Structure formats: C-alpha cells, structure tokens
C-alpha cells in the first residue's frame, strides 16, 4: 500500500484504488497502473522534474529503504494478474531490488523529490510507475 499527496491530489496504484478514489476520480490510466483522485486536505510532496536514474525506495516487506539505479521509463511486459491480463505497462522503470506484491505504493525518491511508486516486481527486480511527466500535478 501507499500513495503520493501533492496539492489537492492523491496518487495511488490503479489496482489498489478505493471506492472513494473512484468517486473523486481526476484521471486514471490502466496501461500505467495509475489513478489520481482529489482530496479535501492539502498535500506537501514535492514531485521531481528530472531524468535521475538513481534514488531510494521504501520496501514494506522488509521495513527498510534501499538505494537503487533504475532504468528510463518505458513499455515493459507484465504477466497477467487478477487485475490485468498480460500486457505492456508504459512509463515503467526497473531496478534490481527486493519487492513482493504488497510493496506496491512504496515511494521512490531522488534528491529532487518523488519519482514514482512501486507497481511491479519479481525475480530480484522491482518496477516503479513514473510520475515525473505529470506536470499538471503541480498546477
Ligand atoms: C510489486 O509487485 C510484485 C513484486 C514481486 C512479485 C510479484 C509482484 C506483483 C506484480 O508485479 N504484479 C503486477 C501489477 C501490475 N502493475 O500489473 C499488479 C499486481 F500487483 F497485482 C501483480
Ligand atoms: Zn531527480
């Protein structure tokens, strides 16, 4: 579990979105596994606007943060799950690191702020849904 709170927005993995998220929907994209909903309280996360390929992520299955080198956002094949059939997920960045399904929502941060959230994993790899291109999160 986990979300990003920036201004009047809440960013979560689309497959983990709640009834409230869907009732206050701003935007959603199945191909990215992202959903943004509105909030009544004000958020203070800083979204990074950069091309960093190093950062730190939170891994709930280990109660620890880990430093990682990660790839540039791209289309990556993802196996079928209970939420999606087998497909290419876009705007995904991979890194070598531990992750389990419950780790989704954990934040990846670089020196500039929030980069994205855990969205996929398996076999010693962890994938993050990028949020740095969503310029509207700020205005
Ligand atoms: C962090 O996730 C994992 C880590 C280790 C092993 C397995 C996973 C799970 C995983 O990759 N998915 C894909 C994900 C998606 N974005 O399509 C949806 C899902 F969470 F239900 C299953
Ligand atoms: Zn950065």
Image: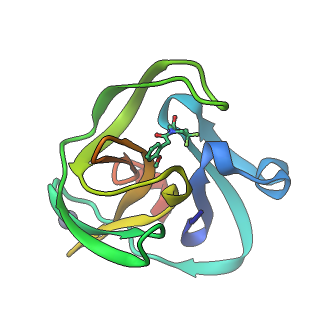
Position in image of residue 70 (x %, y %):
19, 51
Please name the colour scheme applied to the rendered image: rainbow
Position in image of residue 44 (x %, y %):
50, 81
Tally of marks: 0
Q: Residue at x 58, y 19 (%)?
A: 85
Q: In the picture, residue 67 is in which quadrant? A: bottom left
Q: Quadrant of ligand 2?
A: bottom left
Asked if residue 96 lies left or right of residue 99, the reply is left
Position in image of residue 52 (x %, y %):
15, 58
Q: Quadrant of the N terminus?
A: bottom right
User: In the figure, 45 relative to 12: above or below?
Assistant: below
Position in image of residue 108 (x %, y %):
34, 64
User: In the figure, 18 relative to 112: above or below?
Assistant: above
Q: 97 and 72: which one is in front?
A: 97
User: In the figure, 103 relative to 84: above or below?
Assistant: below
Q: Residue at x 47, y 24 (%)?
A: 79
Q: Residue at x 51, y 28 (%)?
A: 31
Q: Residue at x 48, y 70 (%)?
A: 60
């Amino acid at each position: 579990s986990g979300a990003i709170y920036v201004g009047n927005y809440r960013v979560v993995n689309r497959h983990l979105a709640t009834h409230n998220d869907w009732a206050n929907l701003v935007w959603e994209d199945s191909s990215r596994d992202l959903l943004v909903s509105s909030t009544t309280a004000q958020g203070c996360d800083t979204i990074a606007r950069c091309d960093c390929q190093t950062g730190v992520y939170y891994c709930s299955s280990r109660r620890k943060h880990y430093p990682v080198s990660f790839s540039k956002p791209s289309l990556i094949f993802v196996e079928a799950s209970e939420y999606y059939p087998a497909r290419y997920q876009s705007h995904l960045m991979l890194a070598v690191g531990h992750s389990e399904p419950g780790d989704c929502g954990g934040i990846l941060r670089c020196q500039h702020g929030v980069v994205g959230i855990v969205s996929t994993g398996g076999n010693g790899l962890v994938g993050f849904a990028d949020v740095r291109d969503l310029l509207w999160l700020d205005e």
